[PDB]
Amino acid sequence: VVGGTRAAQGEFPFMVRLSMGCGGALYAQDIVLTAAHCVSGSGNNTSITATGGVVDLQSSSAVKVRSTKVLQAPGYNGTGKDWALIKLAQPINQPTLKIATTTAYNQGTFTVAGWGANREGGSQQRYLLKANVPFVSDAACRSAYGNELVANEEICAGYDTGGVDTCQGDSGGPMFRKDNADEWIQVGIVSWGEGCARKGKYGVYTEVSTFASAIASAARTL
Ligand SMILES: [Ca+2]
Image (cartoon, rainbow, N blue to C red; front, side, top):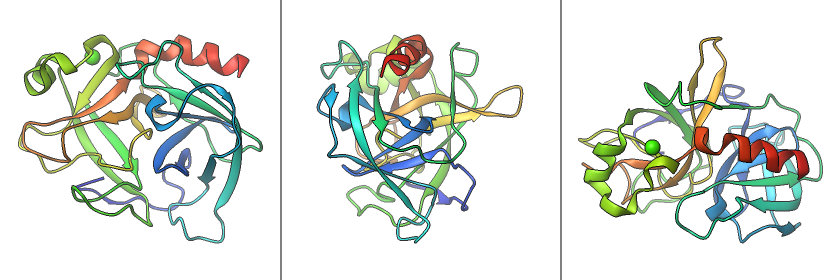
């Protein structure tokens, strides 16, 4: 995350760090929602580790749990549909992040968080960083990215003049905001962008509302 500040311990307890250099959210205590592009595909897999419970990855309170299976979005092949679920062998005992099932919250000021680079080309981070980025219309995003944008499956955010954005290593993490009931709700998954925090180059996120029933469907059978 570029242009952010340190998240406090316990502030976003649903955040998890994945071992291949991605973030994720606890959709269930033993099910991590991340980006399809952070993994190879669906199958029983135990080579991934999720670290939960801490903002400081070096903390003795970190809980590291191994994956048992990976379910990449059905139909994913690199163009849109950027979501995946990772079933954990043990649950991480922290609150889960509700996902948006309607488009009602695809607007406003979002919150992003991750252990990715805090400057384009930079190193990953020890401490979780958070930032706020504004919703950007698909049209504004299309002027920035042209045919690369899959409008009904991607939601954009960031400032036209740059400065605040997710960056390498933040992929897979949740983009969220409050709902009417004062609960965080997930509207996006960090997916891609051109550079980080550049002028005119917004961050692109998986539009969770488009995939919510499919993610829930996958989760019940995972
Ligand atoms: Ca969209």
